[PDB]
Image: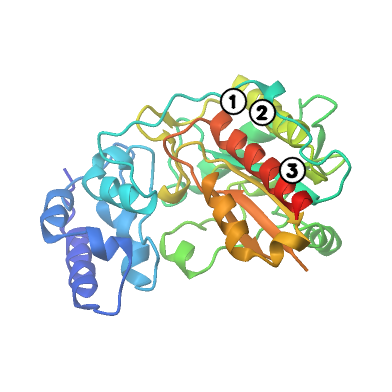
Amino acid sequence: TMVDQAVMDKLDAGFKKLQAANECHSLLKKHLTKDIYDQLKCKKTDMGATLLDVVQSGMENLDSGVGIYAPDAQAYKTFSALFDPIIDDYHKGFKPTDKHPKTDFGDLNYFVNVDPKNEYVISTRVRCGRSLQGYPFNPMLTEAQYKEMEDKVKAQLATFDGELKGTYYPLLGMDKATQQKLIDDHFLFKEGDRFLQAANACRYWPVGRGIFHNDKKTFLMWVNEEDHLRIISMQKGGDLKEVYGRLVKAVQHIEKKIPFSRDDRLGFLTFCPTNLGTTIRASVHIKLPKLAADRKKLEEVAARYNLQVRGTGGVYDISNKRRMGLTEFQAVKEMQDGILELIKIEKSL
């Protein structure tokens, strides 16, 4: 029972503002009805998060797309009357009684090099995210938790095997020449914009924040950016088998000693409700000169595999749209199958 009336007064003011804002089209404004507001405004999670710790960013930033964040893992349940319709809306059909499948990275030998002669795919990447069991998310973390959590992660990164071993760089104390190198690599992150700041998601900066890469720079992690961990495997060319296998290996090593926050209904729990489920985004940068000239066909084929196409002479970033309701294996399989099909069509034009 949230009993802090000064919190409730800020919520009331924020709700009135939301209601009065006719230009606002956030999912928060859409789905925080008076009935739901009144049901949730007096609730709190065990780690002490209130409704304000969920909604404050969308109340301050009326131009938010979604406008809510999870302050801890429990908030998805405590405030399910708001999270559930927003999840349904954003993920395009994931109802309150729907359930995300159990994790399955699947058969790593299903995956192939989708472009063995290096004719199309410039690079391949697979990214996932995790929250660590026992810790709140960015809106509630204290400086001491950021530190203690970073220590715990660093210790596991230090025991990676030969394929994954590398260098951890704290943001605290980072020199200018190192920062520029990491910028050149596209490996640096920095403090978040107004949407994150209003969520109290960059507090105690840069305590607990850091970057890891393996020696060959085919594996990258961010510690305490928008989730506890962001884990990315990448390389030039089209060897999805190698990229995905490296990601699965790394996650398994971390998890040996650090449990993750996973929910039976929603999958892996994240700070932003847009990144639930598998958390996986598999992508290729690919050059398809002939399909470039028939964008309608490129989009039609992509859509059959639930892939998204974004332009960057026919260079595209092609990535999986789906996060909820499928396994990690399925997600990466549909990417593989869709890129193989696009390449077959390109060759046929």
How much space separates mark 1 and mark 3, taking CA atoms? 23 Å
Residue type for callout 1:
Phe
Residue at 87% in and 46% down: 118
Look at mark 2 in the image and give the residue it sits on.
248
Any part of residue 225 in sight: no
Instruction: Please state which of the two labelled residues, at mark 3 or mark 2, is closer to the viewer.
Output: 2
Q: Secondary structure under badge 3?
A: strand
Between discs 1 and 2, the one toward the N terminus: 1
Q: Three-letter amino acid code at disc 2?
A: Val
Task: Left or right? Give the position of 108 relative to 321.
Answer: right
x then y, percent, for residue 318: 64, 53
Q: Residues within 10 Å of mark 1 (few under 14, many from 20)?
A: some
Question: What x and y, as percent, mark residue 11?
Answer: 21, 63
Quadrant showing the N terminus: top left
Q: Secondary structure at mark 2?
A: helix
Locate residue 287 relative to residue 51 in the image: left or right.
right
Marks 3 and 2, Cα distance to the nearest angstrom? 16 Å
Image quadrant where one finds the C terminus: bottom right
Query: What crowding class fits label 3: few (fewer than 14 Cα within 10 Å), some (14-19), or many (20 or more)?
Result: many
**Which residue is labeled 3 in the image?**
212
Assign a secondary structure to mark 1.
loop
Q: Label 3 sits on what residue type?
A: Phe
Most foreground residue, 38 or 82:
82
State which tag comes first along the sequence, 1 or 3.
1
Labels 1, 3: front one: 1
| Contact check, label 1 and label 2, Cβ < 8 Å | yes
Residue drawn at x 25%, y 45% is 79
Q: Is residue 2 visible?
A: yes
| Mark 2 Cα-neighbour bin, 10 Å: few <14, some 14–19, many ≥20 | some
> Which residue carries the number 1 mark?
105
